[PDB]
Length: 49
Length: 51
Image 1: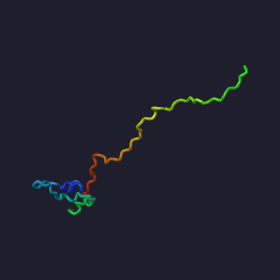
Image 2: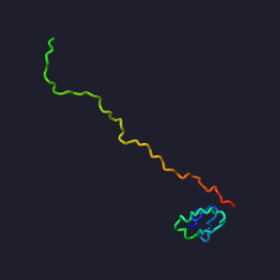
Image 3: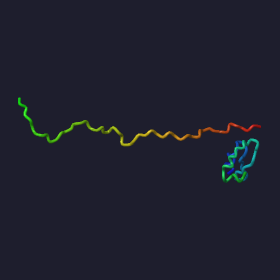
Image 4: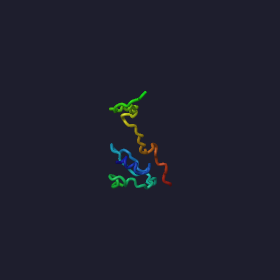
């Protein structure tokens, strides 16, 4: 789901880096986000942002 | 030279050119379907948010 979340925002916002075997996701430069709301199209991940 | 008359003809054979065989092929040849539009390859966000 982190690689799915990284493509719902503009390129640069959610980086997906490994922390002990799993690929967690964190915010990084929220300034870049074009505010296109593409994550609210995704049903599993409109409850995690 | 008298040219007398004769009896009634029984049947009348009609000679005519034959039907055009081997003109149409046994499968049909349709115009192929115009393709559905593709998302073109190499599409990326070219607009960065300012500042």
